[PDB]
Length: 142
Ligand SMILES: *[C@H]1O[C@H](CO)[C@@H](O)[C@H](O)[C@@H]1O
Image 1 (tube, helix red, strand yellow):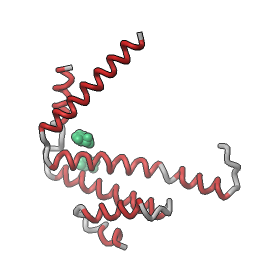
Image 2 (cartoon, helix red, strand yellow):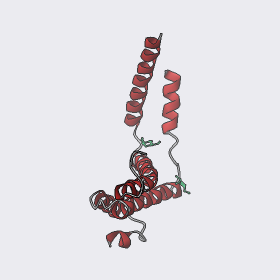
Image 3 (cartoon, helix red, strand yellow):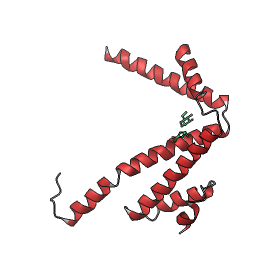
Image 4 (cartoon, helix red, strand yellow):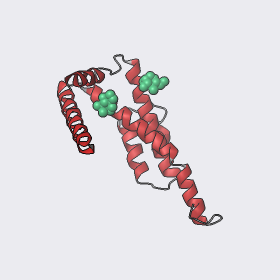
């Protein structure tokens, strides 16, 4: 808004703003699919206990905030929600495919539309490091 149009800097910032919705979308997709993959690699009740403790702490903080302004069932529901992992094998294959595609897209966007050459490096290296889809491997190598 403050930048004067027709300027080079205005065009640069406009391009960065435009190619940022894709960055946010693919980063969120990759992050959530990575979380799913890591939690599915070994679904352990220790993670359930830790998440329940954190949710209880958040409940206590919210109650304290409500007090300043003037549990067990929810813990069990959250534990059940942890049991909402995809209990198949084609589903996790699709999730891994989505994660790899998100990494590839993020690397391509960083290299091309941002000229980063650093974040794209880790993106493509991590994509190549975890069983790529055999179609992205060679373009990512290039
Ligand atoms: C990412 O999100 C999934 C959603 O279930 C979690 O299970 C995982 O532990 C990580 O927080």
